[PDB]
Image (tube, rainbow over all chains, first blue to last red; front, side, top):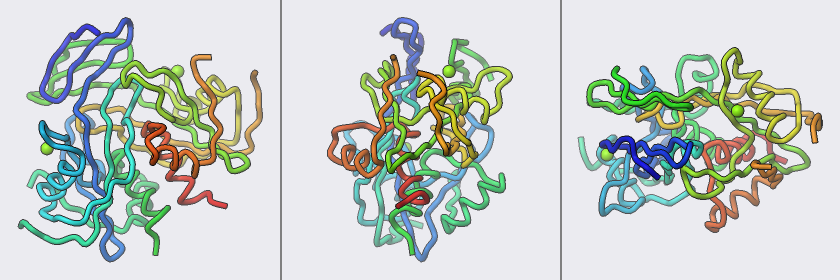
Length: 154
Length: 154
Ligand SMILES: [Mg+2]
Ligand SMILES: [Mg+2]
């Protein structure tokens, strides 16, 4: 593997003819309260709009997935809860190695009081708005919505 | 936006301090038959392993999402079916603009008879194997699994 670029959040390398973007692993947190899911929105220059996502971020040096999940939840929403590991996925294995570890958060407590907008919304409504073309989803946002519809309903 | 690299499936640009990877949009197809979901696996140099995915691929010039979905299903699995658009998502809006359009395929018919391995598997079993750390998921594979558990069960 030969490198063409070493950046802040990514490296661009060539492995033969394959173009590979190395990227730090990430975490995402699914949280439900009173039937609303905890979504967040922020300007995303890469896409030119603010898609509906769930608390997420990169895992930093020294941190493991669970710890990063805690930090991202607190830094983006000011909350903490009991986290449980759910599953993981590669965002787009065809060109990048970014892997995302998803956690479920329960018994949320506000521990703190912005570039990131906190958007509490019933998953049913998020799905409907998307179907109506009013909002876009990030992989984490869609995963949160589908996960809810599959195992957390009522 | 200034470009540092123009490749085959991606461009690397800088928008101020933001590192942005331009990528063609993609499609993914969820298909269930006799309780098994249509997964596919292939060597993915970017991740160094073969994660569990569902039929997917890039949308080529002149093609719209629905047409690309048809092609990817036929080229990777040799099947065709009645496709319905479900939803879309940005794989990782923090650095790339790759957007994936997901479709549901029903009434599958084999129209044709490999780098891509066809893996029919009950979603329940795919989820269990993943939980056991025996298989990894791509975003498309996980989305397929969660979608099934949420709206196609029985
Ligand atoms: Mg961070
Ligand atoms: Mg193709």
